[PDB]
Amino acid sequence: REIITLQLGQCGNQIGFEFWKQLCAEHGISPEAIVEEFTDRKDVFFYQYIPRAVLLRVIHSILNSPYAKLYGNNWASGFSQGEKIHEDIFDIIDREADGSDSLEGFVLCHSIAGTGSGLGSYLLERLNDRYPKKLVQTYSVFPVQPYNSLLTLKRLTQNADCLVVLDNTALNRIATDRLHIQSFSQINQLVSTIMSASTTTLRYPGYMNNDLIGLIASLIPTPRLHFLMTGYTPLTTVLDVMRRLLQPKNVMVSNHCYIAILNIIQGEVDPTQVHKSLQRIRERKLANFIPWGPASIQVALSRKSPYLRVSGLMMANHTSISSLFERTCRQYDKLRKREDNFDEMDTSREIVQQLIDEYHAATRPDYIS
Amino acid sequence: TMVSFLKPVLKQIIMAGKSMQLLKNL
Amino acid sequence: NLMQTLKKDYRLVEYLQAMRNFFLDTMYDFYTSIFDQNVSFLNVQLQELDGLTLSYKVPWPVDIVISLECQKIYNQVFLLLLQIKWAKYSLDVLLQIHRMFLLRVKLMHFVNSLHNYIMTRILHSTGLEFQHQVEEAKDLDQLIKIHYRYLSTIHDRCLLREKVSFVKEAIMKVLNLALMFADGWSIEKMESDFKNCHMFLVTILNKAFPHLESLALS
Ligand SMILES: Nc1nc2c(ncn2[C@@H]2O[C@H](COP(=O)(O)OP(=O)(O)O)[C@@H](O)[C@H]2O)c(=O)[nH]1
Image 1 (cartoon, chains in turn blue, green, cyan):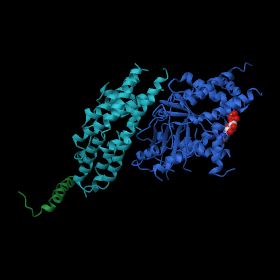
Image 2 (image 1 turned 90 degrees about the horizontal axis):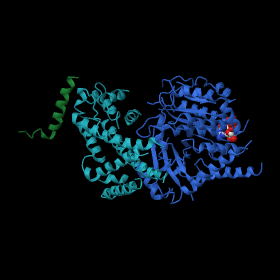
Image 3 (image 1 turned 60 degrees about the vertical axis):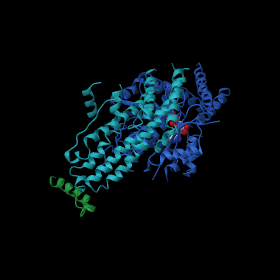
Image 4 (image 1 turned 90 degrees about the vertical axis):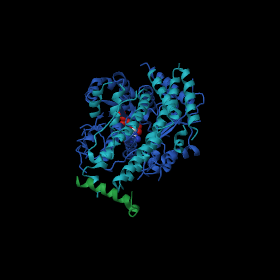
């Protein structure tokens, strides 16, 4: 069961290529798509070796790299251009979808900050049309810009099966704090690490979590609340890791409570001490959950790439993500009264108001009704 | 029915005798 | 000398590692086909409510270690494990109207917590210790004992031997809630049962022998 990737716009093509760089660096696959001599099931993310990549100006830059063997600014502008090449790109998808034995998911790397946001809006409505049994996860990236952003939200609110926020501002913070840079070519170095470590349990088989649906649906309580945020502190026992993870200095997001926590441990840690670490997390109570539903914290063990030290990743569903929406939302109301139908923009503003109003009620002891 | 002369080590004999018989067949 | 020539050359140890691997990845695709029977249909699937007896072929040099009554115990834990993977996957493949979702998280949690307990805390704790023990094998006999002291203990931690109608049946009957609620896709009459059996589960397991507290939190 395989997952196909799609890189949209300058941003998506940038973040995916670097992610494909490190992923090919972790695996024992030389840059020339030829196996190196020098345990890993790689049929999900590789075809016998050519990646199942769908790239969409930067194309020249990708070809100029030695990895050539591995294959306006309006939102409405992107929406129109997508219908123009409707069958042009979907034949590439269909030749690979039907070319794939049993497709499992749809990962998307795109920035909603110009044309990729419009084209990305086109893919979501289109992918739900044809494929009704296919997972759609989007690794969207956040920051005239309020307009393009809010529309992609309206599309992402009901089309995508999941969502992982990646805001540039919080990423800009880590760029100076622990790296001392002030660059686009440098912030993505963390994004690739975030992406690669996210799917480690799928590329290196273990006992639990042998499918992407196995990871996400433990977090998402209801299809409306399908927004996630991540954590990656290591930049030492199992207790040292998780406590470093709950510090808001590390969360990639710029009352409130969590929904569920999933943790990834890639080191050589011992499975004797993990169940006790959860206890000290509960006793010391460094986090609160929903008052209605009994929430749990999950953590999985994995194996680091031998072809490449204890590291870890955290996935979260935190209701504090509502504040991020309200900012652009306020920014929309700002330019709306400040400056052929202009009616769809109001429909987008209505639906995104619903989701936020559900967040604030999601953290109450009466979430029922 | 057993002489206690070699009892304190008898277990190490049988476990060596039978284990040896399975070696010559291999 | 015997143990030395037994690491390779009728590699009994290599065969043992594969044994506990082809069950307890690969076996994910196998069961998923069974979700959506025939006795020959399965074989081609494998070579690619409580039955499915599985066996294996062992050469004489290792026959004395992996005995015949040893296959059944390895089969015993495999049967029960699948029912957990079943309920875990059945409540996972899908995605007062929304009130059903509150019955999902209130349940998809509980089966998920149990699965995290049997596999990680038991089927991987004793497994990590067992390998560190066999690599120091120095005898024909004691290799049986260190092995037989691995099943008869893993059959006890995973509660399947005794106290079945006292404790094990409770987990078994609430597992039927994972089947009934899966098909329907009366609602009020489920939580009255669910909040009862789950409280019945804790108010019975409360007698805790000591390792049961690792799950007693929920
Ligand atoms: N964090 C990060 N953001 C990027 C990168 N490249 C582009 N972006 C963002 O993408 C936005 C511009 O997207 P754009 O190039 O117009 O997409 P296009 O219209 O489809 O070509 C800007 O607001 C940037 O913040 C990158 O490497 N890292």
